[PDB]
């Protein structure tokens, strides 16, 4: 398949959603 | 970062999905 991310917030939002939110959690956020 | 290297038409969703941490 192929997508057309915008590169900036969508590309990073993808890494977080793809699997960049489980190992990207931090103690005490602000 | 893969984001800067994949920044373009399609960004290796596999690289991002495989990136994890």
Image: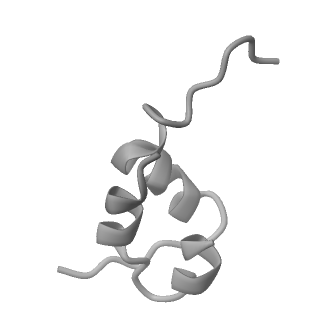
* Horizontal side of residue A29 vs A10, given as left or right: right
Q: Position of residue B18 (x, y in %)?
A: 33, 60
Along the viewing direction, whichever of B21 and A15 lies nearer the viewer: B21
Identify the residue at image location x=44%, y=55%: A14
Q: Position of residue B10 (x, y in %)?
A: 40, 82
Along the viewing direction, whichever of A13 and A6 lies nearer the viewer: A13
* Horizontal side of residue B15 vs A1, given as left or right: right
Query: What is the tally of numbered marks visible in this picture?
Result: 0
* Horizontal side of residue B12 vs B3, given as left or right: left
What colour scheme governs how the chains and residues are painted in the rendered image of this protein?
A: one colour
The quadrant of the image that shows the N terminus of chain A is: bottom left
Could you say which quadrant of the image residue A12 lies in? Answer: bottom right
Question: Seen from this angle, which residue lies furthest front?
Answer: B21
Identify the residue at image location x=63%, y=72%: B1
Identify the residue at image location x=48%, y=45%: A16
A26 over B6 or under it: above or below: above
* Horizontal side of residue B5 vs B12, given as left or right: right
Q: Position of residue B7 (x, y in %)?
A: 57, 82
Q: Position of residue B6 (x, y in %)?
A: 51, 82
A18 over A3 or under it: above or below: above
Could you say which quadrant of the image residue A27 lies in? Answer: top right
Identify the residue at image location x=47%, y=44%: A20
The quadrant of the image that shows the C terminus of chain A is: top right
């Amino acid at each position: 398949f192929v997508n057309q991310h915008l590169c900036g917030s969508h590309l990073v939002e993808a890494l977080y959603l793809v699997c960049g939110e489980r190992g990207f959690f931090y103690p005490t956020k602000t | 970062g893969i984001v800067e290297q994949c920044c373009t038409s399609i960004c290796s969703l596999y690289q991002l999905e495989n990136y994890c941490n």
